[PDB]
Image 1 (cartoon, rainbow, N blue to C red):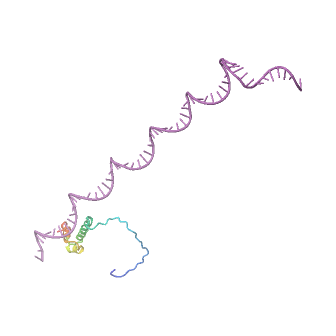
Image 2 (cartoon, rainbow, N blue to C red; image 1 turned 90 degrees about the vertical axis):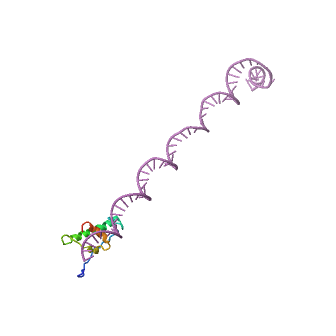
Length: 85
DNA sequence: AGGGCGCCTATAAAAGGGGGTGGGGGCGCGTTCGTCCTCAGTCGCGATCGAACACTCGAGCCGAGCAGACG
């Protein structure tokens, strides 16, 4: 860590074979992919509103632009359309 | 024991029935040939349904442009 080194011994190590997947990874540009993209952004926006101390709760746009910098700001504008002014 | 007698022999002919033997015919008859015939297997559909592929449309997401207000 930042403060120093720490040492443990280990005695047990597992080898994991070939995985049998139980969850389907979406494809690129899929409907499930884009749904997750906007849902994740919406959850981050709600949790930034919960963390806000001023009443009424207020956030800044460039916090979201620091978190999601590949997003066009139009997508963020629409996620803020419903729930913020 | 031996002379005379009986017999078989060759010869003709008839008469009639009986018996023996060989051949032919009958007939039935047994053997051989013809004919039916159905089941089993193959295949050929072709009946049916299920699965795949193609097409259309609807919805969702992203980007861009315009409007409004602050600086």
